[PDB]
Each structure stands twice: as C-alpha cells, then as structure tokens.
Amino acid sequence: SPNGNLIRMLVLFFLESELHEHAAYLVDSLWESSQELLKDWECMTELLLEEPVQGEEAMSDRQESALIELMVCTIRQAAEAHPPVGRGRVLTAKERKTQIDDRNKLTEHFIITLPMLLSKYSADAEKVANLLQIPQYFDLEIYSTGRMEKHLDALLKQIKFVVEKHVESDVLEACSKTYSILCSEEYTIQNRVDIARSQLIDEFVDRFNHSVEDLLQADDDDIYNVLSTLKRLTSFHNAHDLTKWDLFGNCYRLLKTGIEHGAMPEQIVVQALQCSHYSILWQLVKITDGSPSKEDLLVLRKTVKSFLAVCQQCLSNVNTPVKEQAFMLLCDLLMIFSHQLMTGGREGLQPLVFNPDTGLQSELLSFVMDHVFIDQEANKIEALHKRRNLLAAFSKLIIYDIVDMHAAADIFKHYMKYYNDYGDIIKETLSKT
Image (cartoon, rainbow, N blue to C red; front, side, top):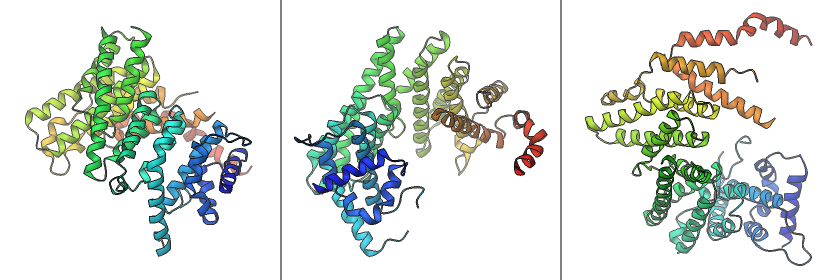
C-alpha cells in the first residue's frame, strides 16, 4: 500500500512536529485536500493488525496510539460531515451522498475489524478507550441487515474481556457507553446486547457482594477485590439502571464502616459515594415517571436522608478526595431534592424535599474556605477547574437560599478583599506598562 507510506508519515508528522496540537485539528485541516486518503480505513486497520514484513520497520507503541487516534478522528469527520468542536452548516447533495456512503463504508468495515482491533490492543488502556469511541458512529441497522450477528457477538466478547481486565475510569466509561449505544436501535440486537450486559453485571455484582463480605467480616486483596469490582459497577451505574441489584445496601455498609472506624481506603469511599448517588438518581427517575404510593416516596426519603447524613459525615474524612466527592454530591442532592422537585404538577413529591439544617450549611461553607480558596504543571489547571466546579455547584445553593446566602457573601467579600482594596491601583498600573 503506497497509501500506507503516506499514513505512516502522517503519523510521524503529527508526533514529531508541534504544528498540530490536536489530532482532530490536523484531520480537519487536511480534510478538504486529502479526504480520500484519510478515509482509507482498510489501510489503517491493516497497518495496525498485520505483523511487520521483512525489511519493514515496525511501528512503535506511540505511533500505533497516534494512528488509532487519527483513525477515530477521520471516522467522526466522515460520519458527522462537519469540522470538530472549536473549528465549526448545510450539506450539498453530493456531500450528503458522500456522508451516507462513508457511514456505510466505516460501519461495515469496523463491525468486522473493531473486535480484531480490541483483541490485539486489549491491554492498552488509552488505545481501547479510543477504539471504543467508534461504535457511536455506526449505522447499527447493518448488524441485522448484513447478517453480521457473529460480529456483534465478537464485539460483545471483546468488550467483556476489556471490562474484566481494566479498572481505568476512561476505559470503563467507554465500555458503558458502548453498551448503551448498542441498545439504541432495533429490538432484535437490543435483546442480544441486553443478555450480554445483564450477564456481565450479574458476574460483577456477585464478585462485589462476595468481596464486601470478605472485607467487612483486612487484606490487600480484600481491598482490591472490593475497589476493582465497585469501580466497574460505579462506571456502568451512570448510564445503566442497576437498581434491581441492591448496590446501595453494600455501598452504605462500606461508608458506615469507614465512618465509625475510619480505616476504609479513600478510593473505596469515593466509589461507594458515587455508586450510591447513581442509585438514588435512578430511584428518583422510576419514582417520577410512575404513579408511586405514600410508601414508595417515604422509602426513598429514608434512603436519601441516610445518604445525606453519610455525605455530611464524609466531609470530616482525612482524605481531601473524599471531602470533594461528598461536597459535590451534597450540592447535587440539595439542589435536586429542593423545592425545585415540586415543579410541573408534581406537588406529590413534597415528602422528598430536603432542607439542610444549620450544621450542614456551616460545614458546606467550611469546605469552600479550606478547599476552594486555598493558598497552594498540567495538574494545576485541572485542580483549578475542579475547584471552580466545586464553587459553581455551591453557588447554586446560594442563589436559591438553600444555604445562608449572607454568610457566603461574607466569605466572598473576605477573599475578594485585595481586589476591593487595591484592585483599582493595580489595574491602572498594569495598563500603563
């Protein structure tokens, strides 16, 4: 493949030079002139899947990662037929025809080759997370049309292998999204994916339940067995309703054990808090869409009240990731279960309304002082945007007077004191320089 040499050098140009920071911007800039080369997906998957021939240099691991990332960018650009975010709308008749044929080409090719790609690179977390961004651009009807049921089985097989081998959050999130996508088209393949997903969840709920009992009744393995299985269940509980498995019960036991004795690892606490939050959100969805009874509402109220106390108690955990996690869920729940919940003819949801007492408001205000306004490279701007999200989620409680909006203003005036006292002098000084 002479196109193979061009693809190889394009990967080299993207890695060796600093002219293009993002792969999506490089693909977009060359899309007008090199669209046919950038859509030779048969050539890209052959470079990734075939072994080097005699006299040919093997691709390094970084070049294979860049080729995968570039390949996914071309898949998006061909399927969506518009530049990526940041570079952005009527398509001509030919462009719409090109999009339909592109969508058909990439769907048939990657329904076959994505299982092969996932199998070869199953251990590489960054590569698998990128490869799992591909099914969202599939024309999923082809699974039934082209009689490609065996390739759906091969994809479901490789996703389960990926879930079983990985604990990274981006990998587990990409697997969860792929399961959600595969159940969003037609019921014949929806039922086949539901069977594979439910069996995958059943196997990890059993392993999680057995690990929780091993831990509470500790070893390094006991800690890993709980954390690793809880990570996969927490990642799937966002997009998948896992309430038929009573996951809140064991998460509550883990959090209560960590509150009394204070020996629970921080990441088990963070995952247990997040998993419990997801369970509550799904329980609210089911209780909202249906016609619940008085017992249904008060059962969820008992659950939310006990979890609000756990999040408040977790604010005193020695580990700051637990504080931030509990604080984010506090600001989330106090906004969801406020009087906002009674909008749109849903006054029957009043028993689910919660008002934070004085002690909780004071502890929420304390977190802002010690963990949002702190004294003291790529992790600095990430922690800054994290603290901004923490303050933004807390500011919504201020606007609607869920917390003491006056006590929060005095905290704001305190940390803005240098700007109100010397800001005018500093502004006009930096202007004339």
